[PDB]
Length: 130
Image (cartoon, rainbow, N blue to C red; front, side, top):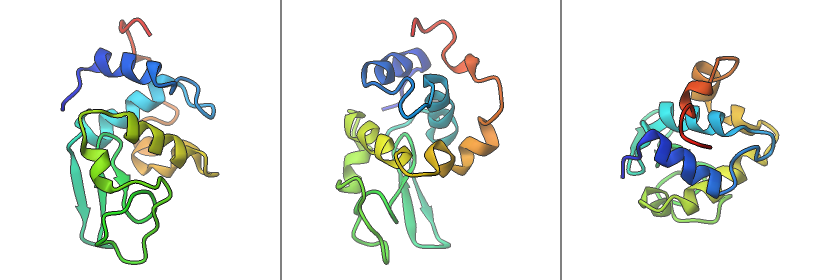
């Protein structure tokens, strides 16, 4: 599914992402925007290390979900990577929460640093009633 901006913002708020481990909702919005364009079925293969990025938050198979074909990988979220391609984002949200519980926090995603860190991110939630 391809979410509309305000629909996603309301969904994430309900799922308790606003302020999770100090990350504002607008940051999570900025991340989903640049990682997948708010698309839950997005997948990106990394030919370089044989891992794959899955779903709305482009979560990596080397550490977070099991896809079976990534060498020397772990599954910290305890999920099949398939779970991250559903229209229902609850499993993807639970995994993203697990990712930020690690020391790097939101910085774990390079796209966040390039596109969201130190910028005016209010734009992503403006007028959504969140």
